[PDB]
Length: 54
Length: 54
Image (cartoon, rainbow over all chains, first blue to last red; front, side, top):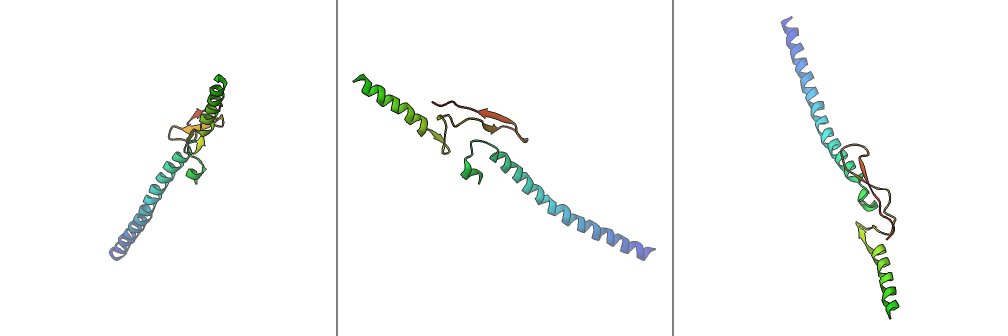
């Protein structure tokens, strides 16, 4: 039980450390989507001509 | 001699009309209709800029 619970705890930390990579990678998916919303909001203005929306 | 100026001024009102631009779009030839501004954070929060031919 002790030896198993120690591998079990080390596996829950391999789980936390894995999650922190995904949770950190999506942290810049937010920075990219927050930027894509702000760009799309700028482009939705009919003062931009074609050369500005491209 | 009045007609010389009433023609040069009528040509001039049409020079204003085709020559005025913002960002390289004509503003007052009357092709500036249905041109929405986007004035908030969500899909389609418009104000519509409409100008008749001048």
